Amino acid sequence: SDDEVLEAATVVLKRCGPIEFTLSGVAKEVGLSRAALIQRFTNRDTLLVRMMERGVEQVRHYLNAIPIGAGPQGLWEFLQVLVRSMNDFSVNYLISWYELQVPELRTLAIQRNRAVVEGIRKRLPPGAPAAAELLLHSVIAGATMQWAVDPDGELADHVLAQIAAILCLMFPEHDDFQLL
Amino acid sequence: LKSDDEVLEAATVVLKRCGPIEFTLSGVAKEVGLSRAALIQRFTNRDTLLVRMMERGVEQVRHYLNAIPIGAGPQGLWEFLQVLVRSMNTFSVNYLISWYELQVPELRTLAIQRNRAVVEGIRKRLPPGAPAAAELLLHSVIAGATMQWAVDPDGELADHVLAQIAAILCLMFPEHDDF
């Protein structure tokens, strides 16, 4: 079923991290034999390259479907949508550690982040400070890590409180950012 | 090698090779030059050893932060953030460490004290008129700019991170030189 296989496989990676992720665990999740998974994907790391190659493509593609909206409020609303969409959890710190380990993964991690910085830019209102998009990308990552270490309330509220704080710095003319 | 300090420094020289997952008393004993039985009686197991290494590290963080001279105005905050950024440190094994810390509650408790130390260190350098909870924003920027450069490097880390740090400082303090 071949694309059933990276679906099942992303569920296994989620469950046990990239060090314990094995072709046998995916063959189990998916209902085929290890033997078949080996001749189809050869190894763990080839299979993570594919799943990621596809992961990069669903991102490029979410970003894109978001139509570029109006004003500082366009940016806020977007950032809100982007942040609420992030789904233990320190498993993505294991996942980002391992992405930097396999050059093929590191390439695609680089493509994923570039892509996400680009979509933030595209939403940037006339005259935003230089590199606002990098600054914004940093707060999102940085504030998510804060919360994973020393969590307080929901992730999104923790992150979004700091994005709204940086959006007031960026657009001191606009009225304080909020929502519902 | 006898003293706990000798042991913990030897375990660093070691946990520089292995990461958390593959760290064993076994290797640490080789390094410091005592038997594995002697590390096992002194440290019980590998995560007790990690805990003690961490506790030292966090104490060293708080002492380091307390020893930086509190200056004044937006300028003293910028010189404090410059020192802190250039201090940490030279980083991939560190994300594996940071992951592992979230795994063992004793370590995760130490990870939270560590973060709050560093957050409270920044808050203390906030001059009047810094926005509400600016110390969380500044801490986020340092962490998040760092992961940004981990993935797609470009220049020295501390330069990537400080550019963004100077840029948010100018937004928080718009009259100043600068920065």
Image: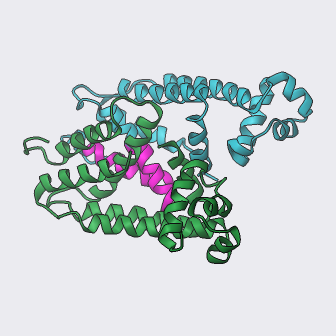
Chain colours: A cyan, B green
Q: Main secondary structure of the magenta part?
A: helix
The residue at the point 11 percent across, 57 percent down is B73
> Which one is in front, B32 or A119?
B32
Query: Residue at (86%, 35%) from the top-left corner?
Result: A27
- In the image, residue A9 sits, relative to residue B61, either above or below, namely above
Magenta run includes residue B131: no
Camera sees residue B131: yes
**Nearer to the camera, A2 or A110:** A110
Quarter-wise, where is residue B114 in the image?
A: bottom left
Quadrant into which the C terminus of chain B falls: top left
Picture quarter containing residue A80?
A: top left
Which residue is outermost to the bottom? B41
Q: Can you say whether A31 is above or below A60 in the image?
A: below
> Could you tell me if residue A32 is visible in this image?
no
Image coordinates of residue A92 in percent, x first then y, are 59, 45
At which x and y percent is residue B67?
Answer: 24, 67
Q: Position of residue A97 (x, y in %)?
A: 57, 42
Query: Residues in magenta?
Result: A139-168
On the image, the x and y values in percent for residue A29 come to 84, 40
Rendered position, B41 above or below B35: below
